[PDB]
Length: 49
Length: 147
Length: 49
Length: 49
Picture 1: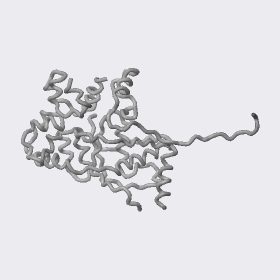
Picture 2: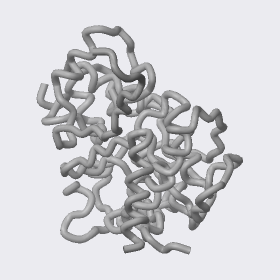
Picture 3: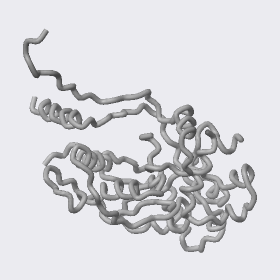
Picture 4: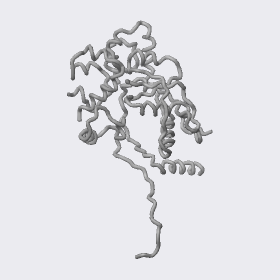
């Protein structure tokens, strides 16, 4: 019964476009076939610590 | 934009500011019955606050690896649909609570309108629940698409 | 022209900019069904390159 | 030279990453247009291209 990420999807803005896009840094996270799981397998293992 | 917010919202005086800022149909904004004024003012000036969607992308990235390492999945598209940016449909859409809006930039093909849609409702039925059971946000999804 | 490209393309907000820049029929740009929007945006902003 | 047999190496999995900014580059888009002649984008994808 994890309550990890809280974001009650309140999405009023996607109804109204023509909104100035925020220029910021990109993640660019590529979920490699095997590595994407391993990252989570380390997090849960870190979560135990 | 500077035309929409101002310092604080105004009782929309000039309709020419509405035509340039946020939509099509300078004709359909010229003619607009003296009934949807209260709806349009309540609509436009409640868009400044309220924007956060971390769990929205969670269901997409969860379904990503559900059919990334596991092979292709052929599925259907079940949705309701909004039409335009600043026209009667977008004004009529605002009404009723618990209605989520997902904007489709290019709704030309079926791929984009299928993935963002299935992402939203509960956890894509009927694709083996197995691990996770994400809570269904306000059901009855309504996408915004030109086509 | 400066009206078309900008710095980078925008989600066409003002239709008055379209009337002066690149065509006739300010009437036929006023009335334009809510279906060819995705086509027109994909059309106009792929003419730079 | 010939002693023992088999073994070999299983290559490790790793992610991929990029130059960090929101906007699209002019070269990669203008040069993508040089090969094909499609009106709208087959595949229906802009960023992944």
